[PDB]
Amino acid sequence: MSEQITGSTPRIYYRGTKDSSVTRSTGSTTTLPLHRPLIMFFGQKGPTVPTWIDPVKFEDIYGSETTNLSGVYCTHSTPFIKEAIAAGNQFMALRLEPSDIPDVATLGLSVDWVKTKIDDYERNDDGTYKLDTNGDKIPLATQIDGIKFRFVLEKIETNESGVSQYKKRTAKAGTIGTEATPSTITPLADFRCRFKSSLGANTALRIWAPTINSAQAADADLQARIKSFLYRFQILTRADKASSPTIFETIYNEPSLSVGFGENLVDPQTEVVYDFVERIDSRYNDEDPSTYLMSPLDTPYLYQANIDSVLTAIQELEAPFDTVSADEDDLYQINLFGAQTVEGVPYHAVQILGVLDGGVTLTETATNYLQGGGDGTLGNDSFNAAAYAVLSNLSNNAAFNITNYARYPFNAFWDSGFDLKTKQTIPQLIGLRADTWIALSTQDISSDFNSNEEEESIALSLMSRVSAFPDSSDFGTPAFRGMIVGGAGYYTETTRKLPVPLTLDRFRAYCRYAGASDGVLKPEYAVDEGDARKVQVVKSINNLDKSWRVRRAQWNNNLVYVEDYDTNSQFYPGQQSFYSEQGSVLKAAIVGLCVANLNRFAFEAWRDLTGTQKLTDDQLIERSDDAVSTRGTGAFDDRLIFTPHSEITQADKERGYSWSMRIDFGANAFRTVMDMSSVAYTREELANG
Amino acid sequence: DSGFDLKTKQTIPQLIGLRADTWIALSTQDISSDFNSNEEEESIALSLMSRVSAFPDSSDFGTPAFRGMIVGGAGYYTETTRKLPVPLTLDRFRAYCRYAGASDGVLKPEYAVDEGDARKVQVVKSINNLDKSWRVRRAQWNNNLVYVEDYDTNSQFYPGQQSFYSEQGSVLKAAIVGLCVANLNRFAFEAWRDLTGTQKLTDDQLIERSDDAVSTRGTGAFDDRLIFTPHSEITQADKERGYSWSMRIDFGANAFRTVMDMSSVAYTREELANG
Amino acid sequence: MSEQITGSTPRIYYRGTKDSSVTRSTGSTTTLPLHRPLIMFFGQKGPTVPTWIDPVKFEDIYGSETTNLSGVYCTHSTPFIKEAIAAGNQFMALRLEPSDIPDVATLGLSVDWVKTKIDDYERNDDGTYKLDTNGDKI
């Protein structure tokens, strides 16, 4: 029940009954689908740069509280995250932070240390069982010289300039035994949180020193084989301030670790390494992209000089004494946190002050929480502020440059309801990149539902902004890669009342259609056939009684809007892009995404052919088209027909270092109007004649 | 516990700490003393619960212990002419001996300890404190004691026979399931005892034979109280060590409903007969 | 009689005898007949926009006083509503309102609050039973 697996002795060990534990889910190798959205959000942990992620790992990369609609991190993009996770799109995550986020949480360990005469107690036998007037016997020796300790665990204070002293603490004057000044506080170790969030303030740790009789019984033979006392270490985390902690297990499904002080504690019989920091940080983390988990704690630090000094002091004092080893190497055997050896014989001449005396009892039931930390100001307002801060500075951001095609394969951006000031920074994505696609919304989810006139004004304002980024700046072709969707409603997949725009519904449709990991459109999910042309995750849509003039004006301004299918549901009469000309090639908004993908295939061709010494012109020209056609054919489900042509023109002959490609494509449109008429006949001349 | 004094009662709970296939029944009565009152019952129950709380089922994760039960009450033995006081643990002991003691290791469906005539007291009479108040009964139930009530003017019955598991889990709420789990723990020992220390085995054969043994031994034995499944393997730590393998059993059970309502509506005879 | 269901303690609770209560009727999925009439009326409650309704639910969507011929809501269309309900036609209801209907009813709760000195009363024991000079004690 207590014994651990010391060695090979024949034995069956019983781990008690337990309740089921969450199992971390393995991931799969990533791929490029035809629909690759970028989603920005507030989160609990995880990296703070764009990351290509497989939905299986979102929960254990960014913490499972970021997707909870009733949590503190909910914003107008959490529904989008949840829909993407449900559908199974590998997508690009970007975790934002508020401008006022505090620093990480910390906890430093120290000891109040002094020397003085203390009392001595009885002993039954060589086992030294008696202490603290056990039985009925008064302490025996009048006064024995010894050492008094009082442990301390407290927040690591920062410098006057606002810089933490994580690595740079120093000793100070103590308070116990101030009758003699040499009473001093000396530090022993530091611990710090890995992320900037309340997870640090809710994380806790335990350290203790077990003996033969503990619940996890220790073994003297291993300590003899490698001379160092072994302490148990544990990490716990709670849900909120009022909940109770739960153990955070190592990557091998263990509840706690054994660690020790020393340079390198290698076990010849089993080659196990018992070093404190190395063992902790190797056993509690896993960076492999498929099995990914990072511990809440960062890498611990130890004050080797001070710990060694205190160990040497106690050895010098009481190592040459009755019931402890005096050898030179027992220094690291000395039990510091406890007051007894592994066998459980108390150290006389060493006194540790209890709780009532201002000390901290390091046992297996005490718990310690890191101090400080926090998330910052959360909500839609701060979310819009952060998103604007990212989007406005795209060409000179020092965090990431998103014109990097190879490193940021995102190709879509959906407007989830940003404010009208942030809305106008989105269109420039299709001006900065040639394989990008955007969906815009005319509703600011933080405000009231717009009326007909307000929707018209916002639509005109967005079209004016879009008109500044023509497709071909050389020839002024109007933009066609995207669409604008008007409307708003309420989310149906939740009991709470949560307004959302219809871009969420179209986002789900596209996730299901063009989200397959193999880069081929699924014919069963055609966004404009069967049941995929109806609204499915929004209810109580507004302005459903539009007049004919209003509907005609919206159509002629190129919005996408819904109508009533029956008394219960709505549908899209036609899903057109915001291309402004009369060409019928570029109307269906899906063709825009198809064209973006073609642009991507061209970049791949260049990437694969650039900078080769022994190629010839004909081989280069041939290989380019081979690559494009091979990558493109059979993917677009008959929405396009395309043909590439590479060559070396006169300008290429002049330059001597370039070749040219040109892709010709064609597509169709749809019909939307119907006539109806009737004529009345007699039954005889209608049935015959 | 057949009526040991309270000093000896407090050294028994350590059996479910020292062994992983043990099941204990405790009594809140000292047969050498006077029949206890309600307050003394409550005090002894709290003391025994405090003692039991020191031996969690899982020391690693602190699962509260669930192998056993506590039974309160006392009476007089009916199978003798003399006057011989006894606690109700005797009656439950007889019931369990009849139910789960067959020499062939399969539970008898005809003696279920909570169906038919086995859910009544049969070898004790003149039980005490049968006029408990509603508050007293509620307190005992919430403290996880097993107590009897009046069936009719002549006899008593057990409204519900639960274990001293203190959590909200409904899997571990019946006392018999604890005995079933103890038997599972025994089967695992048998598997090890059979497979240990063999030169010519392979890892796959070891893993397969462990599960085979546990499943073959357990299937068809528990009269449909449990459903369990074993899984043996060699984890990464086992790879590192080189002389160990792991087994893990998954099991499930049910519970029982205990509260009923009553309501009535008065109709005229015609509209009740047709309408 | 009194105590309510607090937990799982084995027990039987008696809710006394009662006189029957009206049971709300469950409705069925809507469909389109070949005859789909629109009917206007004054109603006790319910929405004030045209609504497609299954006749089983008229009484508990618009209150059961609207179909009463002797009530205050009787106009020259109540017979039409009653015939539709009797036949069983899903139809489109429109509840009109008079041009001078007042607003809704309201009730606010408040406390008159002050601090001062007051009297104190006897106590039998720690139970603090006595109040208002019960028994014979000032």
Image: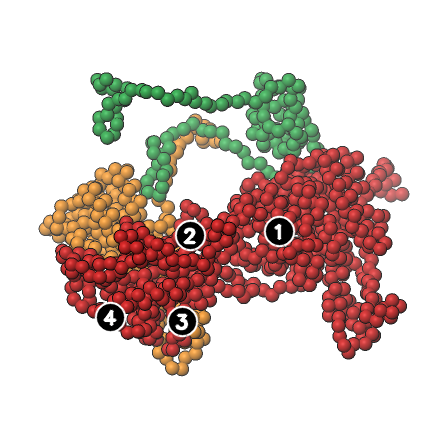
Chain colours: A red, B orange, C green
Q: Nearer the viewer, residue B45 or A277?
A: A277
Tell me which numbered mark, 4 or 3, is placed earlier along the sequence. Answer: 3
Q: CA distance from mark 4 to mark 3?
A: 24 Å
Question: What crowding class fits label 1: few (fewer than 14 Cα within 10 Å), some (14-19), or many (20 or more)?
Answer: some
Numbered disc 1: secondary structure: strand
Question: What crowding class fits label 4: few (fewer than 14 Cα within 10 Å), some (14-19), or many (20 or more)?
Answer: few
Tell me which numbered mark, 4 or 1, is placed earlier along the sequence. Answer: 1
Q: Chain of mark 3?
A: A
Tell me which numbered mark, 3 or 2, is placed earlier along the sequence. Answer: 2
Tell me which numbered mark, 4 or 2, is placed earlier along the sequence. Answer: 2
Q: Residue at x 56, y 64 (%)?
A: A289
Question: What crowding class fits label 2: few (fewer than 14 Cα within 10 Å), some (14-19), or many (20 or more)?
Answer: some
Quarter of the figure with residue A3: bottom left
Q: Give the numbered dot on residue A320.
A: 4
Residue B106 is situated, as x and y percent measured from the top left of the image, at: 32, 63
In the image, residue B272 above or below residue A561: above
Which kind of residue does numbered mark 1 sit on?
Met
Which kind of residue does numbered mark 2 sit on?
Lys
Which kind of residue does numbered mark 3 sit on?
Glu
Q: Chain of mark 2?
A: A
Extreme residue in the front direction: A181
Q: Chain of mark 1?
A: A
